[PDB]
Image (cartoon, grey):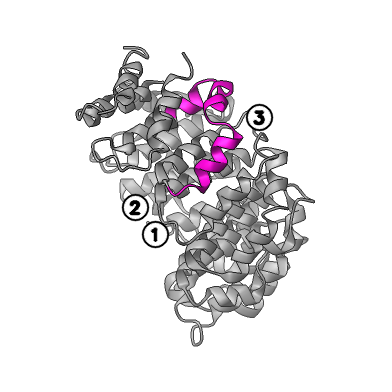
Amino acid sequence: YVENLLTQLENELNEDNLPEDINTLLRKCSLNLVTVDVKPLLATIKRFLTSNVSYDSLNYDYLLDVVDKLVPMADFDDVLEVYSAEDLVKALRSEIDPLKVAACRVIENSQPKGLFATSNIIDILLDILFDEKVENDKLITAIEKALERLSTDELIRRRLFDNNLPYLVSVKGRMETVSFVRLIDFLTIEFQFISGPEFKDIIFCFTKEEILKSVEDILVFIELVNYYTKFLLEIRNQDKYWALRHVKKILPVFAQLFEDTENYPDVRAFSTNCLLQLFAEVSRIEEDEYSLFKTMDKDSLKIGSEAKLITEWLELINPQYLVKYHKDVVENYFHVSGYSIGMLRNLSADEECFNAIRNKFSAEIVLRLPYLEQMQVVETLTRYEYTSKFLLNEMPKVMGSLIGDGSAGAIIDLETVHYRNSALRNLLDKGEEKLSVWYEPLLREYSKAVNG
């Protein structure tokens, strides 16, 4: 019922010849802990982890889950008594994997978060992680979980970027698949907390040559492309615009590789969609007034020209850029059709861009679409205030079809209601004053899904 199930397992672990039904008992202790004496089962499990003999009857899968739950939950001053700084150095450096994973659980939730910054436990953790010989996924995940959690502290970020600073850049220059990709996911997590000075140009930024070197094993190139897509996003979200200067000029290298198909063909066949997502962030980043992306566009990318790409450019690139420089492209491609769904979604973000396609938009077109797409379009037009102005008053037969005087299709929905409902709840958020002669039919139709 309470801790009586975990203090039951306690006495069976204390037993010299463990009750062979120790697997079925562990199959309950671990699943019952999911619901939620402080140092009983901490030292009792510790004897199995430190135990060099293999346990076929005692499947650690569950024994380590009991620790993964107990350790973060129970008081850390009690957990620090069983597993101290001295206990961890012996545990991490040992060649007993369950003990190593359980040690990560202690380093995981350190109290305070900069407790083991004095000790070189942070250093040991990296030497296991950036070690291609280690393939135990459970262990690698446990080292990352602890790192991501302790990276919140000042004392940990400095120890990670000073003592391990050479060992980090070493792996970076080495470029070993298992290790280097492990460095990409590490540095991304680290950049979320790393301040302006704490930035070490070499470990965070990769030079043109290194990106050309990653081309070899396409798998690395995609995560390296991903690394920079992640970087430009944490620049606009955390407003870390000091990190812009550091990357800046190494981005057009990706634009070159995307243009070249003769020399680099696997780039445009294994990372086309991935690189597209990277370019969209380049157009969106803070620059006066869109020059870095403009250079990439005029020299390599070439927005338009490539027929099979026009769709995606109007589907991913910043509309604020697309309006000021490719106004023609927007007018001569995107129209009302159950394919331009994504084009409408992406181009709707700016008023000037949406105003350029007011003409190409017409009430009669929306009505001839299947009710699925019909709603998709309505939903998309209920995203902003200026799009509401064009839906509520300009196309009322569309708004009238949203309520469905009868039905402009009916009844099989699948997903369509999610779109209908969103469009219904989004219009209602404007207030009775804004909705005018639609506040009553909209509040009525939306209530049909929340109750029914």
* Residue carrying label 1: 339
Residue in view at x 46 percent, y 31 percent = 425
Q: Is residue 293 magenta?
A: no
Q: Does residue 92 belong to the magenta stretch? A: yes
Q: Nearer the observer, disc 1 or disc 3?
A: 3
Distance from label 2 to label 3 (Cα)? 59 Å
Residue in the image at 65% along x and 57% along y: 284
Q: As drawn, which residue projects farthest toward the left?
A: 21
Mark closer to the chain start, 1 or 3: 3
Q: Which residue is mark 2?
A: 369
**Where does residue 28 sit, x and y in percent of width and height?**
27, 25
- Residue at image position (48%, 27%) is 71
In space, the residues marked 1 and 3 are separated at their CA atoms by 53 Å
Point out the tag, 1 or 2, that comes first from the N-terminus: 1
| Residue at which label 3 appears | 112
Judge whether 147 appears above or below 447 on screen: below
Bounds of the magenta segment: 69-95
**Helix, strand or loop at mark 3:** loop
Mark 1 and 3 residues: CB-CB less than 8 Å, in contact? no
Q: Nearer the viewer, mark 1 or mark 2?
A: 1
Front-most of 448 and 183?
A: 183
Residue type at numbered disc 3: Pro
Main SS of residues in magenta: helix
Of 234 and 446, nearer the camera is: 234
Report, in whole angstroms, how far the alpha carbon at label 1 lies from the one at label 2.
11 Å
Quadrant in which the N terminus is drawn: top left
Measured as percent of width and height from the top left, residue 46 is found at: 43, 31
Q: Residue furthest front?
A: 16
- For this view, does 403 lie left or right of residue 173? left
In percent of the image, x 53 and y 42: which residue is there? 90
